[PDB]
Each structure stands twice: as structure tokens, then as C-alpha cells.
Image: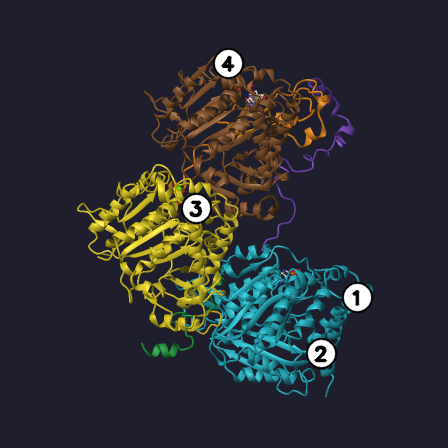
Chain colours: A purple, B orange, C green, D cyan, E brown, F yellow
Amino acid sequence: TFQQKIKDKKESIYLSNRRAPLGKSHDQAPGLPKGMDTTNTTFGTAVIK
Amino acid sequence: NENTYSNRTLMGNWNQERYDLRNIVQPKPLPSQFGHYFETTYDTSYNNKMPLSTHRFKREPHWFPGHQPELDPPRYKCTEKSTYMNSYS
Amino acid sequence: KGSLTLRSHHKKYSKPVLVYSWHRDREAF
Amino acid sequence: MREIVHLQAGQCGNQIGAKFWEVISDEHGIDPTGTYHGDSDLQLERINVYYNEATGGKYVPRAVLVDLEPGTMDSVRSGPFGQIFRPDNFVFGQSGAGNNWAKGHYTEGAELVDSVLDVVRKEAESCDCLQGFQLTHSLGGGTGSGMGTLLISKIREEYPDRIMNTFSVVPSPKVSDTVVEPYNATLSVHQLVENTDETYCIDNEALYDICFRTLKLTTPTYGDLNHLVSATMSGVTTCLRFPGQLNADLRKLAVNMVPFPRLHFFMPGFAPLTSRGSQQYRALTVPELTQQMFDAKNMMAACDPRHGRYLTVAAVFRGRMSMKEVDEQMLNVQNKNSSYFVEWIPNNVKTAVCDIPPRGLKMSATFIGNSTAIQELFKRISEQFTAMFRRKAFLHWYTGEGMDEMEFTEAESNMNDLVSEYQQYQDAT
Amino acid sequence: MREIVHLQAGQCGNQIGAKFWEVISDEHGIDPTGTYHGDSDLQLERINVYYNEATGGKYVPRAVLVDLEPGTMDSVRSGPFGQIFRPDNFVFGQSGAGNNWAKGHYTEGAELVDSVLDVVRKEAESCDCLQGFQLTHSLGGGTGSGMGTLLISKIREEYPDRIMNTFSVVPSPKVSDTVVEPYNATLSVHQLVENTDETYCIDNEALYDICFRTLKLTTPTYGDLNHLVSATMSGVTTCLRFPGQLNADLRKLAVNMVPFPRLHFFMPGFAPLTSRGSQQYRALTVPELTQQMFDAKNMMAACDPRHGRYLTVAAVFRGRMSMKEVDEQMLNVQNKNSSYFVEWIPNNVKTAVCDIPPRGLKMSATFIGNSTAIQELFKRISEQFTAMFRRKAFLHWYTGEGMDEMEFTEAESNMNDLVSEYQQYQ
Amino acid sequence: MRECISIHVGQAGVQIGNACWELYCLEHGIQPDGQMPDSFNTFFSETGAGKHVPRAVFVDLEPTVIDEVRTGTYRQLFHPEQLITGKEDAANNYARGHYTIGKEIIDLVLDRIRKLADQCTGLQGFLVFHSFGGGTGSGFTSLLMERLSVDYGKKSKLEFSIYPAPQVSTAVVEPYNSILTTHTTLEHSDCAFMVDNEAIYDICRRNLDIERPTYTNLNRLIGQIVSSITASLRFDGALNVDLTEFQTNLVPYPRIHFPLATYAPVISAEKAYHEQLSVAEITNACFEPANQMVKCDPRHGKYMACCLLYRGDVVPKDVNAAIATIKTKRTIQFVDWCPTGFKVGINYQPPTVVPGGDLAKVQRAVCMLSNTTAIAEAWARLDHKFDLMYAKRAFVHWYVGEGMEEGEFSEAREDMAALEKDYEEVGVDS
Ligand SMILES: Nc1nc2c(ncn2[C@@H]2O[C@H](COP(=O)(O)OP(=O)(O)OP(=O)(O)O)[C@@H](O)[C@H]2O)c(=O)[nH]1
Ligand SMILES: Nc1nc2c(ncn2[C@@H]2O[C@H](COP(=O)(O)OP(=O)(O)O)[C@@H](O)[C@H]2O)c(=O)[nH]1
Ligand SMILES: Nc1nc2c(ncn2[C@@H]2O[C@H](COP(=O)(O)OP(=O)(O)O)[C@@H](O)[C@H]2O)c(=O)[nH]1
Ligand SMILES: [Mg+2]
């Protein structure tokens, strides 16, 4: 498993590996601002009365 | 008639024996090397990778052969008070 | 049930609430 | 000493009735515990109208809450003022009606009314002078329409000489919220015309427009709409519980506003509504309130006053005001709208004045209209019914339970008769 | 105050009695040493029913262990609970009967009962108010069926106005564990019916069905089969030693369940039985216990109740529980199954409620039932007995020990009359 | 001065008297230790140290249920020798407790009656709490009521007996023990209040909303009745009744002494405060057939005599206005030789609630003791059961082999067959 981790660390540089991992989207942390936990924050406009 | 195997091999009524107290208190080994050829979609998505520490269960009375009072919450473990001692205090 | 008792006639209410014969009950005070 | 029995049927009727009980409990100074906490002694003088005394100096409402589901009943019970009610009057079933009028009136609602009329008889036959009944419901459903009109029919059958006030939320053109709404609207007017004395129509689109333009609320929730309906509801019965110069009870309104036995669908209103942005700039005067009554945007039904004629106008003012300005203004409006009021009935307008205003405002006014322009809603309901009935869509759910096809044609004939009477008495010299 | 004297005969009776004296030593908090280690003080107010006091707070059972072969007396002694039994409560010889009724009843079992009746009369006078006698044995054996029925005739002459109660192991239709088992079953049953008031028939195939089908076990050894039997013996006497809402002793069961002097053969059952998986997922309520008692799959007798009519039924409950749901459920099973009860008597079901469930358990119940479907048990032996007798097979093992052939003639004549009696009242 | 001696026989008598004597402690404010922190002298006799001991008797043939009292909360309140225990029960048999095991313990019980009567400067009578369906409550009772009549001649002998239910049941041979105990309740008794268990199972379901009741929920409703009957002796009121006073207004013939018991209102704590409990409403719940504490419908029968016992803030005007409404009801029928069938007893004290109880705190209450002809219907269904099993001679050897003859089965059927025959003769309109 450690040798496969070596292989995947070397293989992570590919365009296909950046664009499309298995069962997921790409990395969204460049897109979102730094230090924001994505699953905790709320997206949208809050309606206030 | 039927070829009886060990408990691990999923053959016959393995489930009740896996519910038995012995197969509960047996430990579960850690994930090992050459374990990436044996990962499935259900294991990756709907399971937990935390190592599990085994549990030891204290001895209680048994009334019928299938009885397992070890896996019960700490309730009705002592003799119940009667109607007089419950109502009239 | 609680409706098993009779639906009954008349209800007492109280002294500030004015009902029928409130004037006649006041007259004896 | 005159008593009104309240009934809540359907989800919309249940929520509006709960808001009504909250509003009039705040008017009478009753906390949700059940005691009395007020400053004026005029609140307890007439509390036998809506409430029963209990043991220990507590007060309970004289309403029953019926719904075929246990959801809205639990919501009302867990609501703010749900503690004051009595638990024996909480009569409910288990199986939903599914917005089926046959399920509301024939199969599931058949077994519950034997218990509903028992508690209705309990709360009614112990009254000193039963003035009448007041039911809250909606037209477009299966529970609020079917078993609602069933209760109306049986109560009218067993009490022949009383008065009924049915406050009904009606279908609307753009704010349709049910697929079988023309069918369940047409299936209840056949019983509403025959066995009801005053039917008050409420339109959701009109409530939305009032909350957007006059009030300028940004978030007009169903709580706000039900508050509007309840505040209009209590105004017509202020005169049975509060003193005034010119008292007018429910039969007073019935005699003054029902000229023909089959024209008793009324369009109501509340008159001092304003936004707090312009509350500072608007002046409270009797002529300003009088102009505020007859605004078309104020009207709480989706009908245009410009597209018809007015039969009868009623206005109940609350507060301290002189009477010459009221009579002069409500003669001036009839003079200036000469071509719109009917000429074969002079003096189209009845005014009443009460001495107690609502809490939080100097004066108020409730406006009720009986007009020939209400035929547009019945016309569009009949047109939708014909367009669905040509191809018989959604009809097997009714025919598979015990409903015949011919009752649909009978109800359509009664709708056509009603709009014919409206048009005939509009165009008559 | 109301003392039960236990009698154990044979190899089977000794092996069950080790398990029976294990569970009520477990119920009262009695350690294998002999002292008491419990929590509540209601476990000692009536403990003299089963245990005699001694010095140092030692409790010893009031039980006698009898067998003509010392093979099983070295195993009941070398068991877990083998020290609390009194050393003077063992009576034994050498030549075991070897599945012969004559050796246990006339020749070898004749001089052994003199020492046994010396022990019993020593224990009987030590009780303040003796409640009755209790016995367990096997009808298919040599010592239990041979000598244990000789005591039943012998004791009932000394103390006639008492309660006799047996838990006898009847032969199974299919397992066929002995060649001459219908001989020793026929001769004992002919002697049982006039010297017994309560007979709970237990059969090994009926218990083997329960572990496979209800308990879901794959290795049901004799240590499992004896435990269900020992649960029934505990649940019968549960109101004799514990408080409750409506009590019932050994006399109160026998007076409701026995309408006629020859109708005293009962058909046992126990109630809260569930597999290893179905413990955390099943709610112990009164409807679930009543649904399980009356079903034929949870029965300890190898006879189908659906082929006969229940004469009278007893239900003995345990635990803090509600009496209205008790009375509603066994009225509903009487109302729905109107064809499975005789119509010349109303209220075939008796009620008994205690307040003490067993430790670790919520509610428990025991099913005691008279039925006319136990005549199916006796007709199988009676058709087996005449198949061997018409060829006069195996007879020299019986007539060579002082027995005439008339005890073979009468024993078929009496058992044919009893199955003629169950058939009349159906 | 006026005081009652209570007798409790059987397991029913001990467990009814367990939930009855907890209310006599609470009404008079007597602690379980036996001390207070002239009305109390009807049951509690003073001691020079300040202790109050009940003047009751507890009898059973088994010590299984009385030993729980001796080791319970009230182990100090009761006298040590006031609770008589046998060694062996009668076990669902009338023969055992009347001839064989009921004879060795009657000398101790009869000695305590002669002792408790000595401290009584004036005795009104006896009250009995027992059960028909048992061996002690019907077998030991049958010779005790024979024995009490000889020693004390004209004393009142009231009775609160547990009648067998129509459908639910506990023992198999209860129709035998119900038959042979009615021979002693006819001439050695004076007035017999029967209740059953099914009719109180119905009450706790539809009124108190308790889906799963027990005996300790049933026993407090029976314990509520007897404290309402005795309430005139203890506390001041506008018009008191006496134990001799309400037998005269309720028993027209010496063979007709079987009333029905009814109590109202019975509602829980939550439901009570939303309703108003008027004097008209509590006296109208009693006349409904759903509040009968015996499973009999009074529409089939005819009322002969009635008695009303009132507690709390009752005004005599509204009692007269509510009774006059009842007399205009066509559903309620009275027999033509009783033009005046009402007796009214009024007491001041409102009822008291126990901690942990099911009933609510109320201001007024009423308990009607109604004699009616609709009890011969209940006695019809028990003889339909008795001859259905006696025809096949079931269970007979349990009785003859213990000491009676088999001829007591035939006569005790013939004894009460004429008793049903007398009910339709009374019900004929004159
Ligand atoms: N309502 C009610 N009934 C009871 C109560 N206790 C006992 N019973 C009645 O008593 C019957 C049971 O028989 P027991 O009274 O125990 O029998 P017994 O009078 O003690 O006679 P033996 O048991 O033979 O000694 C049941 O059918 C119940 O109806 C009680 O607390 N409340
Ligand atoms: N004002 C108001 N109207 C409501 C509310 N809930 C539902 N409605 C109206 O009720 C109509 C649907 O009726 P429905 O609830 O299905 O009838 P029911 O099934 O018999 O209860 C919709 O057109 C809504 O406009 C509410 O809380 N307030
Ligand atoms: N259920 C059960 N049956 C048993 C046990 N021990 C023996 N048996 C049965 O008893 C029969 C043999 O009894 P046996 O030893 O000959 O009796 P004995 O001659 O009096 O000693 C066999 O058919 C077994 O099935 C036991 O522990 N449990
Ligand atoms: Mg008893």
C-alpha cells in the first residue's frame, strides 16, 4: 500500500488525475476562499423578516 | 446431506453463530498490506475505518440456551419490587 | 368519556360575568 | 347571553380558527393558561359568547376541531394557544381524505360525524340562547369541503331556525394549489346555497396583493394571511359582545343583507390597514377611512367592483367618532357612485358603530359587500368544470367509491342557475 | 411453611435433577459452595421450601438421588453444583436393571427401597407443613421406570393426603433409543394412573424440535434439552415462594386442571423463547407471550393439540404486568378457537400471576395443559406393545424374574381403557 | 361512639383492605407510623401513648399475602395479632375452607371479634370484604357469617363482595363456589353490595384513559365507594345517614337485599379542569348504564329503591332540581309500589386524593346504591354455567372427598332457583 501511495503521488501530476478522480469531482479549494469548511457553510440568500 | 464449514465461510446459518458471544468477543485484525486489492464500493462508501477495540462481557444467569443477558442495557438486572412495594412505597 | 356525563342545563359562570337573571341575583345582595 | 358555536374543518380552516382564537383571546385579555389578565372591566361583561367558565375560574373556548388527519391537530395542540382548548373536543380520525370529496362525504367522513354531532350537541343544548354557528373551511379540498358541507347540512337539518356563518377560502385564478379544485369547488356550492345563511369568501391572490401593495410586507407568510382573515372575522361579531351607539347583531346583518334567499355570498374587508413606512404620514380621519373602504385593492376577493353592481353594503365602525360625518360620507359615496349601485333599491348602505376599538389602534372599520360582480368567480369555476368534464378527467377516483356522474351535472346546473340569477337581477329596471 | 420434597430416580432423573437444582440455586443466589450471595431480601423469606438450614448459613437441598448404577452418581457429583447435595442423600447398588422393569420392581429394586424410605421419612418429619412430593424419571429405562414407580406406590400409602407430581420422559415415536422401551412404558403407565395427581409428560423429539426451529441452534446437546425442562419445573412453583397479584400452589393447579380422577395427564409449555438474533428486536409484551404459548411449535410433548380438544388449560405468569391485558388475551383465544375447546365447561383457562420475573428477564409464563390429544401418545405405545406381545418376544427377561404374564395382560387392558375415556369426552 | 368493625376474608379482602385502609389513614391525617402530626374514633382506637390502631380483621388461609403487609410500609399501624394467617390455602374449593381447613383457625378469629367488641362502647355492625370465586373468601366466609349471627343477634351485616365477571374469569370452578355460598348470604346477611372486575376494567379505559390497569387501580375505586358510604358517620353534614338508616330505605323484603354500586364523577387530573362538574352532571352520570359497576343493564330491569350519598359543596336546592329532571325521563322506570324511591344523604367534606392516584381532586361527588331487578339476569348466566358442568358431574370428587355430601349441590341450586323466581314476582305491576 505504501508503494502504491508512492506511485499515486508520482501519478497525481497528470491532467486526467487532476480533472477526474474516481467517484468525485476535482479539488474545489482553489475555487473557494481559503479556510472555509465547505460542508459547514450555507450557500444562498437568507430570507429575513 | 450438508457440508459443515467454519463460521467465517458464510455457509449455512452463519448469522446466529456470528451473533453468539464467542464470535463477538473475538478480535478484528487491522487492515494490512496487500489490502487494496480487497476494497469494495460498499467498504469505501458506507463503512468506517476506525479500528475497533474488543469487549469483554460479565457473567449473568442464563435461563434458556439462547439467552444472552450480556448484551442488554443495565435494566431489569435486579429483582423487581412487588406490587405492594411499588405502589404503597 | 368526559362527554359521557350529561350535557346538562344552566352554567354558573361567576359574579362579574352578566348572564340571564344576573339582575335578579344582584337584587338579593 | 347570545352564544355562537365555532367549528374548524380542514387544514386551512383549522389554522385560521386557531389564529382567530388567539386574536380574540388577546382582545378579551385571556392568557393561554386560561385565567383573566386585563385592565378594563368591559372585557368580562360578554365572555359567554365565545367561552365557557370552568372549575377554578378558568375559561375554555366554545369550538370543536375536526380533521380526518392527526397532523394539523397535533400542530394546533402544540401551538401557542393550544393549551386553552378542551381535550374531549379533539375528534379526529386516522386515514387521510386525499382531497377526495367522496372520501370526505361518503366513506371516511361518514363514521366520524356520529361523534362530531355528539360534542356539538353537548356544547349547544346547554346554551342559554344559541344564536348560531360559525365554521371555518376551504372550498378546494376533500376534507374542508366534503365533511364541512356535511356538517352544515346536518346541523341545518336538526336546528331549523338559526344562523350559519361559513368562512371559506375560495379557489383563485393564478394561485391554483390543487389539481381537482374545480371539481371539489363545484361539489360544495350545491350544499352551500341550500343550507347556509351567510357564506364569506376569501381569496389568496387578494391577500397576497394586500400584503404586497398596501402593507408592503416582504415575506407574507400564511400566518399573516390567517391573521388578516381572523381580524376581518372578529369585526362582524364585535357588536354581539361590545357596547355601542347603534348595535347590529348577526340576524340584523342577515335581514339587511339577504334580499333573496339564494344570494348570501359576501365579500369582506378590514379598513385601517397601512404600512409603517407611511403610518407616520397618513392621517386617521373618518373620511380617510371611508375612502379606504371602497378601494378595489382592499377587496379580499378576486373580483372587480368596476365589473358589476352593488346590492348591499355593510360597514361596522369601531371607536369614538361622531355620526353625522359617517352618515354624510356614506351617503356621499353612494351619490358619487350613482351608476354602480342598483336603482331599484335606494339606501344601499347600512352603518353600525361600536364603542370599543381594536387593541393598538384608535379606530377601525369592517366593510362587507354583497355585489353582482361576484358572478365572475362562479363563471370561471363553471368554465373549468366544463373543460374538465368534457373529457371526464380525474373522475374514476370519484366513481369508484360511490359517487354517481349525474350529481356533477346537477351541481353544474345549480351553478348556472346561480349566475343566471346574478345576471338577471343585475339587468333589471 | 410449604415444603416440596424432590425425588430423583434413574440415569435420566439424576441428570435432569442436576440442572433443576442448578437453576433455582441460580434463582435464589445460592453459590456452588452453599452460602448465599444475592441483592434483594425477598429471596430468603421463603427459601425453606427447597433448602434446609444448617450451621454457618449453609443451605442444602431437600432432595434424594436414587439409582441402582453408580455410573451417573460419579457425574452428578463431579458437576458444577455437585457439592451442595448432601452426602447421605445417595442410595445405590451395583446391578442396574439394564432396561428391564422386573429387576427394578421385584428383585433388585426391592431391598433398595428400605434405605430410600428411611431417607424420605427422615426428610419428611423435618418439615413444618409438608406441601407434597415431586419426582422426575424416565419411563423408558430400567431404574427410573422400575423402581421410581415402586416408590410412587410405596409413598402414597404412608402419606395419602398429599400431592403427587411427576415429570416423566415418555418414549418418542421416531428416535427409538431402546429396543424394549414399549414394555417398560406400558407397565409403568398402568401403575401411574391410580397413584398420581399431576403428570407432565416430556419427550425428547419435542425438545429437539424447539432448539432447531425456535431457538436456532446447531448443537443441541443434553445440557440444552435439560435446561428447558428445568425452566418448566421452576415456573410451576413460582407463586409458592414469591409474592404476586393472584397466587397458585400445587394444589390449586391440580384442582382446576383435573375434573375426573383419570384425567390427570398434562402437556407442558414455557413462554419467552427466542433465538440469539431476536433478543434486541422483539418486545416482551403480553400479546407476544400469549401468541407463543398456544402455538403447537413451542410444546414439550410430541402430540399435536390441533388434533384434539383442550379440556382445561393453566397459565402461570410472572413479572410486573397488567391484569386487564391478561384477561383480554386469553378470552380472545377462547373466543376465536371455539372448535379447539369442549363446550360442556366454560372458562377452560386458569390465571396465576407472580411479581418476580427471573433475573435478567422481563416477563415469563408457563403453559400447563390438559388435552385429549395425549391419547395419541398412548395409542402408539399400545400398538407397539401388542406387536411384540403376539410373538411373545423378549418375554424371558421378564418371566425369568418372578413376573407372571398377567401383568402384561392387565397393563394393556388398563391403557386401552384410558384411551377409551379420552375419546368419550371429546 | 358510633364505630364499625371491618372484616376482610380471602386474598380479595386483604388487597381491597390494603387500598382501603390507606385512605382512612389519609382522610384523618394519620401517619403510617400510627400517630397524628372524635371522627377518627369510628376506626382508630386511642392509646395512652398517642397511637391509633385500626379495629379491622384480616383473615386468610395462606400467609403469602399477609406477610407482605407485615413487612411493608404499614407494619407498625396494624396490631400484631390482628392479622390472622393459616398455613395452607383452600385452593379454589368450597369444601376445604368450610369443613376441613376452615375449622382450626375459626377459634382464633372468633376470639378477636369477642375482644374488639369489648373496647366498643357502642357497635353499629359488621362490614365484610371477600370474594365469591375463591376458597377462603367463599368457604371460610360461609361458616363465619353463620357463626356471627348466633353470637350477635340483630347487628347489621353489610357486605362488599366481588361478583364473578360475565366474560373474563380467573378460576375454572368458580360457578360451583358461587352457588354454595349464596345459601349463607340469604338468611345470614342483611344487604350485599356486589361488584365485579369487568365493569371496572371498562371504567378505567374510557374515563381515566388508563390503557393497562391493575388491581391496585381497581382497588382504589372500590376503596372510594366504602369511604363514601361511611362518610355520614364520621364528618358533619346537613343530613346524615346511618348503617341502620339506609337498610330501611333500600330493602323491602328480607329476601331482596341485593343493590348495585355506582360512583361518579370518575375523570383524570388533566380532563377535570376543562370541564365543569355541576350537581346535575354528577347525578346524571350515575343513571347511565355505562357507569354500572356490575355488568347489567337497568333498561331491562326496573328500579325498586335508591339511595344518594353526597359529599362536598352541594346545595339542597340543586339536588331537588336535578332529581326532578330524572323523574321526567321515560327511560328510567320505577315499580308502581314505590312512588317515593329516593333517599338523600348530604355530607360536607369533599373527597381526598391519594398521592400517585388516578382520580382527580374534586369538589363534589355522589355514590348511588341502587336496588334493581336486573340482577336476576346476572344470576341467569351463572346457572347456565353451573348446570352445564354439573350434568357431566365434573369436579365433584374434589368436594365430596373432603367432607360435604353430594346433596349440597342439588339443594343449593334449588335454593337460589326460587330466589330468581321471587324477582319476577316482585316485578309484576300491582
Ligand atoms: N377487583 C379485585 N379483585 C380481586 C382482588 N384480589 C382478588 N380478587 C378476586 O379474587 C379472585 C381470585 O381468587 P382468590 O380471592 O385469591 O381466592 P381466595 O378467596 O383467596 O381462596 P383460596 O385461593 O382458595 O384460598 C379473582 O377472581 C379476583 O376477582 C383485588 O385486589 N381486586
Ligand atoms: N390563507 C391560508 N390558506 C391556506 C392555508 N393552507 C392551505 N390554504 C389553502 O387551501 C387550499 C388547499 O386546500 P386543502 O388544504 O387541500 O383542503 P383540505 O385537504 O380539505 O384541508 C390552497 O389553495 C391554499 O390556498 C393557510 O395556512 N392559510
Ligand atoms: N431429555 C433428556 N433425556 C434423557 C437424558 N438422559 C437420558 N435421557 C433419556 O432417557 C432414556 C434412557 O433412560 P435410562 O438411562 O435407561 O433410565 P434408567 O434405566 O432408569 O437409568 C434415553 O432414551 C434418553 O433419551 C437427559 O439428560 N435429557
Ligand atoms: Mg387464597
Identify the subunit bearing mark 4: E
Q: Disc 3 marks which residue?
A: F406
Q: Disc 4 marks which residue?
A: E69
Kindly report the distance in space between the C-alpha atoms of the residues bearing marks 1 and 4: 95 Å
Question: Left of F236 or right of it: where is F391?
Answer: right
Res B87 seen here: no
- Furthest-left residue in view? F48
Q: Given the image, on which type of amino acid does mark 2 rest? A: Gly
Q: Given the image, on which type of amino acid does mark 4 rest? A: Glu
Tag 2 and tag 1 share a subunit: yes
Which class describes the residues within 10 Å of circle 2: few (<14), some (14-19), or many (20+)? some
Q: Quadrant of the C terminus of chain E?
A: top right
- The image shows residue E166, relative to residue E96, as above or below, that is below
Q: In the rendered structure, which disc, 2 or 1, sits on the residue that comes first in sequence?
A: 2
Q: Quadrant of the N terminus of chain E?
A: top left
Q: Which numbered dot is residue D389?
A: 1
Q: Please state which of residues F265 and F342 is positioned toward the viewer in this rendering.
A: F342
Point 29% across, 48% down: residue: F56
Which class describes the residues within 10 Å of circle 1: few (<14), some (14-19), or many (20+)? some
Q: How many marks?
A: 4
Q: Given the image, on which type of amino acid does mark 3 rest? A: Glu
Label 4 residue SS: loop
Q: Which numbered dot is residue D308?
A: 2
What is the quadrant of residue F366 in the picture?
Answer: bottom left
Cβ of mark 4 under 8 Å from ligand 3: the answer is: yes
Q: Given the image, on which type of amino acid does mark 1 rest? A: Phe
Label 2 residue SS: loop
Question: Left of E98 or right of it: where is F107?
Answer: left
Kindly report the distance in space between the C-alpha atoms of the residues bearing marks 2 and 4: 115 Å
